[PDB]
Every structure is written in structure tokens, then in C-alpha cells.
Length: 244
Ligand SMILES: *[C@@H]1O[C@H](CO)[C@@H](O[C@@H]2O[C@H](CO)[C@@H](O[C@@H]3O[C@H](CO[C@H]4O[C@H](CO)[C@@H](O)[C@H](O)[C@@H]4O)[C@@H](O)[C@H](O[C@H]4O[C@H](CO)[C@@H](O)[C@H](O)[C@@H]4O)[C@@H]3O[C@@H]3OC[C@@H](O)[C@H](O)[C@H]3O)[C@H](O)[C@H]2NC(C)=O)[C@H](O)[C@H]1NC(C)=O
Image (cartoon, rainbow, N blue to C red):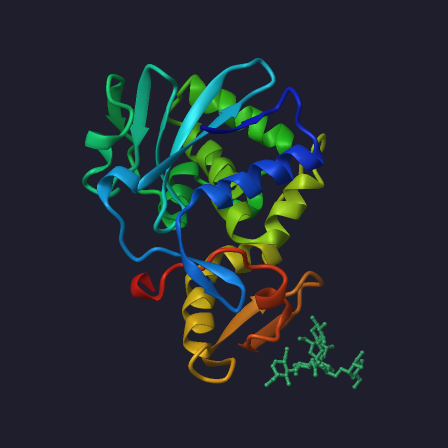
């Protein structure tokens, strides 16, 4: 499995991990030089596994749906935990031999924030936060897990989707930070950006519908075509148009 360990964590090793995560996903080609995910795939190739290891050498394995980069489940090696409403074939295909449990929420941000009783902007990221999240999930506690899963998802799925997010985390190897509204805006608009970039291919680079983001200085900005920085040097994976 593609693996990230905290014992050797550096900015460079984290970037290498995210590159390897991206590379492990099958692609349906590129649009404006950005890889597009598959629309559908056979069950035997539907999931990839990633290992995350804390400072104390304790590992969890997260299962990711290759069609959308969603984490669907994780395992401690002996017990596994599945989100509500994951693809129906996931339990049969993943972590066979473990004791399989269901988490009391779906993996969407609305439901995770409700379960955590706090917002993404209230929850620290950075590699020390990843260490704590791994520990919380390895020693599963129902009250603490949603916040830990929010850390895990943003540090894997969202970093894979956006270079900007990857770099913010890579810049916090020994420190912690709470994500800005710039980060939150990218996460919220991944599907919308994916849709518009694929539409734009048949419209001379023009979006059908604008996407509103927050720039690093906190300004509202309107994205209307593929010449914008978010398209040319940020987004790294597109959700297939079939799923938008
Ligand atoms: C495809 O899309 C691009 C858009 O990415 C099309 O071009 C770009 O359009 C944007 C939006 O209109 C434009 O940005 C704005 O520029 C205004 C002018 O800025 C110049 O002049 C002022 C003085 O008048 C100077 O202060 C500047 O330094 C600069 O020389 C600017 O006033 C706008 O800012 C206002 O809004 C922001 C909030 O978003 C506030 O913060 C400001 O106080 C103002 O109220 C705006 O500037 C952008 O602001 C957000 C920042 O994140 C950006 O970095 C900053 O640019 C771009 O100038 C324009 N880009 C180019 C290269 O032309 C493009 O035509 C289209 N391409 C196609 C169709 O092929």
C-alpha cells in the first residue's frame, strides 16, 4: 500500500506521498492537462488502500473509492469502520477478516461537522494533527472520531485534489494551523470546478456557470474560464462529468 509514516516525515516526503496517492488512481485521460477520474470501474479495481503511521509506529489503513477520492472506510488491522451510505460492494471487498463496524454518520462534511460538533475551520491541520488523528482512530472513541476523520480526509483526499492544500499541509510539518476560507472554498467547489472545466473544453475555455472562490487574501473571486490560477496551477484531479 502507498504509505506515509510520521517517523521520517518531511515536507518532501509528504509531497511524495500525495504524488503517489494521485498516481495510484486510474485516469480517463486529461482535460487542460488535468487528470480526469474514471466514470465507472470493475469492482476488483474500485478501491485503493493507503497506510498512515503515527510517531509511535501504529498504523491505520484507509480505503479510497477511485472514482471520487472519497475515504469509505478504515482499518486498525483487526477492526474496520465503514461510513454510512458507502458503495454497497465496499464491505464485501475490503478488510475481509476484520470485525466490520459502521460509523454513525456519512463521510460528507455536513454530517461529519454535526458529529464533531464543530466546523472544519475550528479543527487543526498539519502533520502533528495527523499524528493525533491516527492515534484517535487506532484507539477508536466514538465522540472523538469525527474530528479525526475530518483531519484525515483533508490531509489525503483534499491534498490529492488541490496543490494549494497539499502545500499548506507540507508547510506545517512541526506546527498546526486551522484551514482558511481559501482552503474551505476549494473543498466545497471541487465538483463544480470539475464540471465547468470539462464543459469548457467544448466552449473555447469558457465556463457555462461561474464558480465563486475565496482568494488567499480573503477576497471573493469569480472564476469564469480555464486561464485562472485555480485551473492552471492548483487543481490536480477532476471528478468525471458523469458524476457532477
Ligand atoms: C478569463 O478570466 C480572467 C479572470 O481571471 C479574465 O481576467 C481577469 O479578470 C479579473 C476580474 O475582473 C481581473 O481582476 C481584477 O482587476 C481589477 C483591476 O486591477 C488592476 O487595476 C487596479 C487599479 O484599478 C490595481 O489596483 C491592480 O493592482 C491591477 O493593476 C481589480 O480592481 C479587481 O479587484 C477588485 O476586486 C477584488 C476582489 O476580488 C478586491 O480585492 C479589490 O479591492 C477590487 O475591489 C480584480 O483584481 C483581482 O482581485 C482579486 C485578486 O485575487 C486578484 O489577484 C486580482 O487580480 C484581472 O485583472 C483579469 N486578469 C487579466 C490577466 O486580465 C480574462 O479576461 C478571461 N480570459 C479569457 C476570457 O480568455
